[PDB]
Amino acid sequence: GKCRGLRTARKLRSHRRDQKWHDKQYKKAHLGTALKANPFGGASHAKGIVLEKVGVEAKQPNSAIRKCVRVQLIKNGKKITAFVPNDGCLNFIEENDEVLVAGFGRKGHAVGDIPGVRFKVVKVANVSLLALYKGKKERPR
Amino acid sequence: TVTIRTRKFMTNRLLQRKQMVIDVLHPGKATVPKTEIREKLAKMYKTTPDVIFVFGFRTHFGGGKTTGFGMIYDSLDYAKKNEPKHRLARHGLYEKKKTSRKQRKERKNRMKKVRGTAKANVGA
Amino acid sequence: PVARSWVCRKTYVTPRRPFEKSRLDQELKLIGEYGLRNKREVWRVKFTLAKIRKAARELLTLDEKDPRRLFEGNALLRRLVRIGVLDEGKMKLDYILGLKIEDFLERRLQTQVFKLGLAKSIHHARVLIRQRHIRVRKQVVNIPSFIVRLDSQKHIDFSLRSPYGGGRPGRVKRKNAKKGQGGAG
Amino acid sequence: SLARVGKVRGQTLKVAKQEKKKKRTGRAKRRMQYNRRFVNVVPTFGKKKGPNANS
RNA sequence: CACGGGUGACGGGGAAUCAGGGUUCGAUUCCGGAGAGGGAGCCUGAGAAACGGCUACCACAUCCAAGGAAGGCAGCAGGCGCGCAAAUUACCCACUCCCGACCCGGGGAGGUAGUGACGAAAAAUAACAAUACAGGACUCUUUCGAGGCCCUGUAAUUGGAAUGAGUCCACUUUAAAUCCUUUAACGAGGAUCCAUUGGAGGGCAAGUCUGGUGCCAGCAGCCGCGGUAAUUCCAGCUCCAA
Ligand SMILES: [Mg+2]
Ligand SMILES: [Mg+2]
Ligand SMILES: [Mg+2]
Ligand SMILES: [Mg+2]
Ligand SMILES: [Mg+2]
Ligand SMILES: [Mg+2]
Ligand SMILES: [Mg+2]
Ligand SMILES: [Mg+2]
Ligand SMILES: [Mg+2]
Ligand SMILES: [Mg+2]
Ligand SMILES: [Mg+2]
Ligand SMILES: [Mg+2]
Ligand SMILES: [Mg+2]
Ligand SMILES: [Mg+2]
Ligand SMILES: [Mg+2]
Ligand SMILES: [Mg+2]
Ligand SMILES: [Mg+2]
Ligand SMILES: [Mg+2]
């Protein structure tokens, strides 16, 4: 504190209430602009329809072709370049299928080698991509 | 080898009964039945076993002790005066009707629709 | 609106650092010394120790000759004496802070059976506890987490329904006797 | 391009899993862990090797 | 800091994280408020602007002979839609009480069961003995080796001893059942009656092992790894965390 009077409670409280808005986490959490820009809308998971599969070129030094899916959501209709996590799991994902889409753990931020991808794919047509990778379950055909 | 002790003895003249918590010790066997409980309380208290009603056994862990409640009425008329009909039907002197509850509700809502003497003619 | 408790509490608290080598060393030594089942068995005794030490610090922060302080101190010393970790001459609220997880694990019924010596090993004592061969004051104890009181320490013996005690033999002995009589005729 | 999906996963050699005696679990696993950590080994000079250390 | 606006705000007792201070949540079983699709108005009645009461308008929707009639599950179950997201169209007034002309009747309030890995507590998946071995406090021996009063561990080596999980008669439980506890008879040596979930460069405990791939596939929350000897990918073995 700077003003150390005996009755400066409204001064200290109003100064701290003004200066909380310059924090990055507080303003993002307490304004609706970030919640509007979020495609999930304050949700942890979201289902969406596959429409096309995208080969995204990688960033600087690491040079590769990541495999993403243009997901159109149901709850909003927004488009997400969702990420296919494991090896060889793009072949399980076909066109016009409902897939479950989650975050990647950096709370809405692009991670590592992949430019402009915040979200990833968990389940494929009510069958999990982890079980499709391990070989436990089969795609329902 | 079955031993019955009584705890918390009380005489209800306002209910015309005796009451106690029954402690049964039965090493080497399972939980003894309520008929044998009533017979052993009858030969203990020198009364007829018809007035003795015992319910609510809980067996301790390990398997050598149970806890149950029982009352000893003066007469069967007093037992039918203040004793629940379900515990009377446990032994068989009372028999409840077999009209099921949802069908009774349906019959009541059907009798609610028709006004007059024909409420009896709605049912069957 | 239903008639039930909804009252529960976690008896264990996980530590702040997951991969401390010295902490895993100490907990592994504790489990290998006193015959435990997991790290949660260490953590719940550590959290009860945290409860007792927090109550002890809350009593030491109070002033002397306070009635709540004297009552809670005498009650906590009575609890430590009756569980038998603290001595009956050592009972003072300043000595509660100098108390340890090893002395808490010494009062386990598994460890008490091992120290009385009716079992061969600590895990064999745990097998006896699981298979219900022992009793405490005519009551069969099936769970090794029984905090044995000092008053009820000397009453530990074999249960009545036990082939290791005075009872009927087990399934293996009955099957071997039946196979022997069938082979004999 | 998206034609190389699952290339290495397809072209690795399919090695069958070796049959193995089942591991003891729970308190017996932690007891056997304590026995292989402490009471077997002796303090030796030099740098002590790890559990999975091989050469 | 009025007024106005927003609330992804019913308020409180309280919940979580917590040194001391705070921060976040509280629709949710207790108290008070509001409401029965959206407003508005009224009869009865001590008490209602009541909706398992009516009267009109709007939205939705049923039958009709085309004149007309009837509806309000943000009650209990259940169905559609919406979704990342949530149970049985069960049994009973026996426990708790409530109402009635009342000891007798009624109560989807409530109680008990079916689903249930939201979560909390306890807690099986082995232990012992004998052989071979690998070693430690003694004695002896310069070392090599030896005796066991004392040991500790390992090895699909062998051996009986003890039990559930399950099966299942019988009590007990209960309004009637179910489950727990008890109890006969079965039930275990790869005790196949087989425990998984993640990782092994550092943070962060744990292989510079082997084969393939060769900036490709992919791994990687951060730094980074892969460009033909990968401690970081994909598989086997081993190990580590719970
Ligand atoms: Mg970089
Ligand atoms: Mg609002
Ligand atoms: Mg609101
Ligand atoms: Mg509230
Ligand atoms: Mg109202
Ligand atoms: Mg509605
Ligand atoms: Mg109304
Ligand atoms: Mg209604
Ligand atoms: Mg109402
Ligand atoms: Mg759920
Ligand atoms: Mg009732
Ligand atoms: Mg009645
Ligand atoms: Mg209800
Ligand atoms: Mg198992
Ligand atoms: Mg690997
Ligand atoms: Mg690491
Ligand atoms: Mg390390
Ligand atoms: Mg790595």
Image (tube, coloured by chain):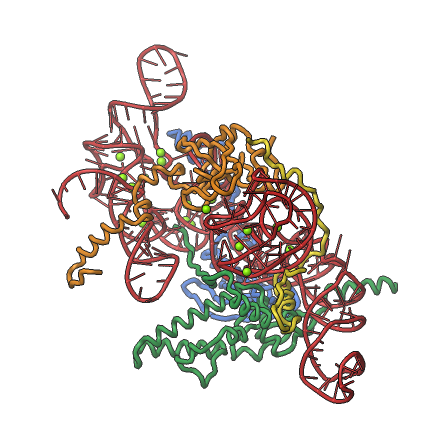
Chain colours: A orange, B blue, C green, D yellow, E red
In percent of the image, x 54 and y 34: which residue is there? A125
In percent of the image, x 43 and y 69: which residue is there? C50
In the figure, A84 relative to E20: above or below? above
In percent of the image, x 38 and y 72: which residue is there? C55
Kindly indicate the quadrant of the structure image that contains residue E209.
bottom right
In the figure, E113 relative to E191: above or below? above
- Work out which quarter of the rendered image holds the N terminus of chain A and state it: bottom left
In percent of the image, x 41 and y 54: which residue is there? C3
Instruction: Pick the residue in front: B15 or E114.
Output: E114
Q: Position of residue C149 (x, y in %)?
A: 51, 76
Q: Position of residue C60 (x, y in %)?
A: 35, 77
**Left or right of A105, for residue E101:** left
Q: Position of residue B8 (x, y in %)?
A: 47, 70
Q: Is residue A17 visible?
A: yes
Q: How many marks?
A: 0
In the figure, A91 relative to A18: above or below? above
**Left or right of A50, for residue E34:** left
Instruction: Pick the residue in front: C141 or B2.
Output: C141
* Image quadrant, ligand 2: top left
- Work out which quarter of the rendered image holds the C terminus of chain A and state it: top right
Kindly indicate the quadrant of the structure image that contains residue C162.
bottom right
Q: Position of residue E220 (x, y in %)?
A: 51, 48
Q: Is residue C145 visible?
A: no
**Furthest residue toward right:** C185
Instruction: Pick the residue in front: E54 or E61.
Output: E61
